[PDB]
Image (cartoon, rainbow, N blue to C red; front, side):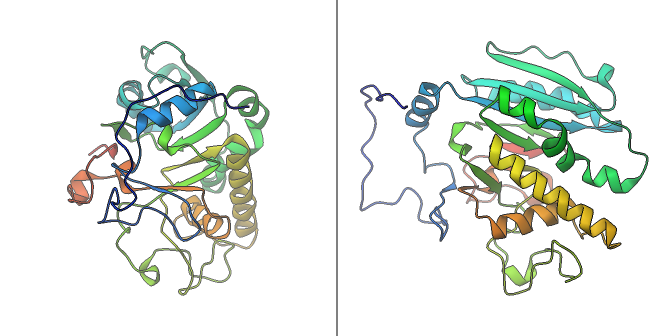
Length: 284
């Protein structure tokens, strides 16, 4: 049950003026594409706080990548869901190497040790398997939404409840202006991740997806199962779990799509006019 919003004073939305005219802000299946200027964060914060929303953030930091945790977590504290309840789940092979990061009130961190796996096949499948096969009951009990991101990143600007929805993917920064035939989908019909040249909405990046716990578990389960089939058939998708994520999101449309504000590499791609903010960026 959702209680009434309080009285709020904010600028009136005007029907005969778009928020953005330079970009697509809704997909053909009526999912918002989230760009700066499309949302009033005050309204959204109210809506999500009134539900006492808890967001889980999963991040894998394996081998040398543990070195990225400090900046990842410190910047998440500055920019990720501030004001809301947040539970970080750090999956790592080196629990002792996790930095001691000071957290704001209402935010917690759990260190989850993984796992075994001395063959690259299981490593490739590790993340999808971990989210769907091992942490299933815990996530359902502890958080409302799950967000799955890469560690070799930093937050530079607001990443907040505007992204929350049953299921979201993020436009890959390298390909948002590309035609579908150019997308690096898996193109071999022998792979479960196969997408023909005449199919595809967007190319989504494996580095930032999420949704409700239930929808994320469905996605990660399906991707893990598809990857197991490929392994049995002696094939590895061109971009690993990202290829499978793309197949899943073609066949199960996301209910929001994040713009490349949410996943950017400034060293590689600069700062285009279409990006008013660079929110979450690759570490050079």
